[PDB]
Image 1 (cartoon, chains in turn cyan, yellow):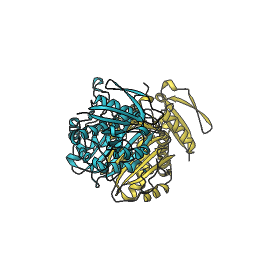
Image 2 (tube, one colour):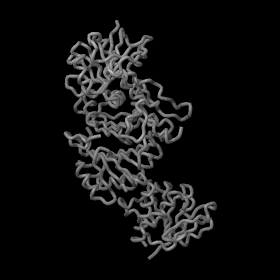
Image 3 (tube, chains in turn purple, cyan):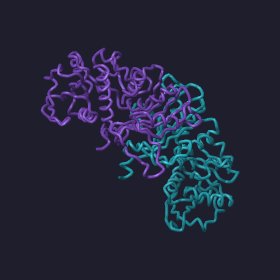
Image 4 (cartoon, chains in turn yellow, cyan):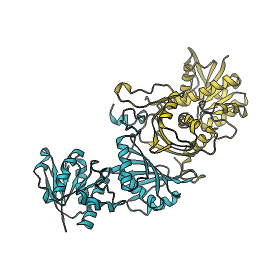
Length: 306
Length: 302
């Protein structure tokens, strides 16, 4: 069984990464379509040994495809995802646009793959922010074991918007709580994915002068005590996570290792407070994390619903 | 009344900063003596409109001095402080060496000026780590008002070379740091011990994360405080404006004198307070703190 797939925003960095991930993950693609604006039309890419030509989204017949991956910015998704959906395409959307819609599932496949069933509400599934993906993958085993009462998290990214490959702010006027509109969005994404309005989330989204890749410092207040050693064991077993325990010798120092893996380290309890757990979570290639999450959604969608 | 003051480690950066702070604060100095090893002897500095020559510590008569400010490294304080103290000098030591000794006070004048009294034990007062000083001045009003149950703090260094490495997110995974058995570095534990000592409170839990990546302009700290009674971030923002030496910043662009910003409660948890603390010259902070101790010593003890 093979499926027709579109990538919208195919000439952008995430869109290009999506093609690479579909190939690397050996997704059962029959025909691949690459969509962009008129200015990008005619550009060529190689996928599974075949040539694919970018075409204008304005001329595209959506009846050709089963699933579309969108990564061309929120306003274009706002316009085009309803149109693809109406044609019977299931859109996996890598923008902020549909993440907060009550009727649209927001999915991290290691955490809430059950939510994918709700694709039939609107023919759209929302891909979360890489920051939220990273954190939720790392926290889920802890949540499952002992519960989570409160998360305090600091995220770090470049001031310039570059560094997303790693290989070369407005106060929220409604909440009036001192958190920025980005920070509140993380709260809402986190609570949605956990499907748990009782989890308190307190983010600080920090811009750093110069930074390649993305990092988060995470403190969690658990509902039952848990030893750092236990959570390190859990994370080591968990899929998609690479745990770094630290090196005593040069030969024990490791590189990033994975293509799109959640890199975890500095795992430790609050001193004399074992219902407090601390960890840092890193993504070297931010785009590959986002793209991979989107493809994992498509894999499960195809498996259980097609 | 004027006092004879020595600086040991005069040619080091902190030593030079101490000279500058003594001058800027108009400390009542009779004679300033500048001390170092054989090699640095003969070097000159300007102080209070005078040329002062660096001399060898090995040949120095300590009976000349009332107060000495030390910042030549831990082993040298270990060597010279008991020697100076025996000669009747009150030593204010900038190193970590004496900080954790039960009979030596560790003093931040805004927080625990009472502890200076314990200088009579061994004629030594310990100056805290520059990052601990920075944090404790910001937390003191909060501590006084509602108390503090738990502090979680991250300290950041200021801005293949180290410069480039400090820009790579993968280095936030601390593969090559040396950890004590509880998962924390010596450096981080020192912060724990200094905080509990200065607040004179063995019950305050302290959880420090001391990092060299990412880096910010100035010396930044991110603090979460778990209080003993709820307090509004607006109350807290009021207190910090009505405290001298602290400057408050609003706006979501922070980190961007001691500066304090992003002050907010944990959502629906008002006994949680979050804030950033940024110092422009954290080394000058340490020097200033040491000179402040010397000031209270002169005023209240001499």
